[PDB]
Image (cartoon, rainbow over all chains, first blue to last red):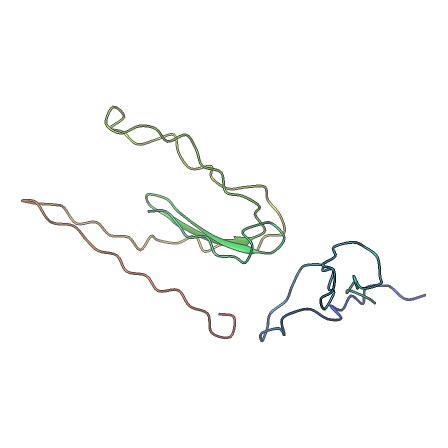
Length: 49
Length: 97
């Protein structure tokens, strides 16, 4: 069933600079009713695998 | 002066750079630190001997290596007044370095 350590940041607001990592999670929305909840719809959660 | 804080949010979420300078040493360190602590400092002229200081860091985390080496600050003897040294620093970032 996989080792599940395939965490990729999916999308974020800023395109990364060279040799730069982000140890962070996000509640990226693209903008409508600014939301920080864990719900998938319109409060999309990055770091899939 | 003692050290400079570099970071994006000044929290322990990311690795934030700190500098700590001893009287005969310097410590340059990047790691995750949430909030620097300031020791008790209300003393002007009664305590001529300066001690009971340092211990300003925060809780440890996944830390990189430090750069303990000889300090860069040099002091000349102030003779006949108006004899002090101006220190200049430049910090920048090209390709992460």
